[PDB]
Length: 330
Ligand SMILES: CCCCCCCCO[C@@H]1O[C@H](CO)[C@@H](O)[C@H](O)[C@H]1O
View 1 (cartoon, rainbow, N blue to C red):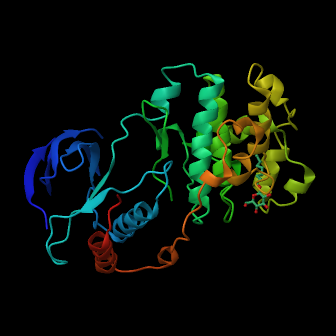
View 2: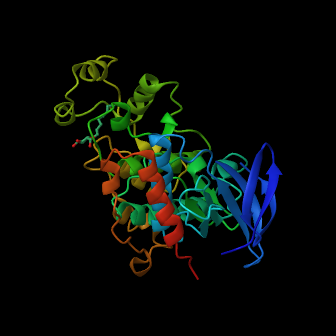
View 3: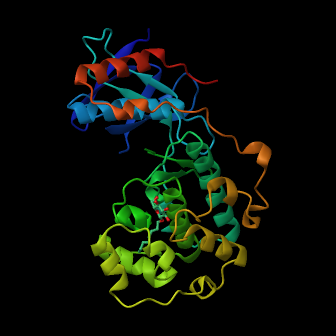
């Protein structure tokens, strides 16, 4: 058991092993720290008030379980988790240590005009990671430029798994449960923006957002209208005149036609037909990066705990168990 020291930053006290030095406020709260053990810079996150409620405590537990499970070059992972508490009874603080990422994809599309090769590399990395996330049975559900860390070498990690601008339309319809392809929709929106320097669907609210989407992909085939239980949703789609399905070729003139085709296959209104991460990784557009022997899948992931109402002390105790059972990587 390590040596802890204490420190006031911004407004909050931090008690962390001595192994971590020069804590510097970045973003729970996030300090950047020097891992004296590895020489590497890392991020130390102090969860806010981890066991403030049933909702907070289950989330804390969920966040710990997720991060413990994620072992892939393109998905945020856990370097360490600790707590100053020395018993279950003391336990009120949780810290997570991860690679210091320092820039997001927003800081990348916003202050540049990326080339085609750059978009192949970034998107390929999203999809490689997403394949691993999906093969665990996890849907991420909030993929957007700000949940993607991109280091100075253009290496990418997916952050925060399990803005309306990237949300699959079926989510905006509420829709009684949906599938992994809700993520492929997001990816298609991210790609479009990488290529164009423009937000694809900068909807003003959830209604507008549907309009903007329809402008591009066209009003649903009767075979898709057939699947919408909601009459008011039905009505609104059939209202606002039947819209002209655009040619992606014109919306994306100048883009590599391979990029354009792939977009067409991602931004399909019917999540059934939307291309999957596994598939998209084999699309020609990625021919320079693809390698089926280096696109691993995840060990299956236990999320049965999502289907239960437990007490705070129960979520707390399970979280305590996970901290203590953490085994670090190489
Ligand atoms: C703007 C109008 C929105 C177009 C309809 C969204 C199509 C989403 O697709 C639908 O998603 C559902 C949720 O998984 C599935 O149950 C259906 O099989 C699938 O076709």
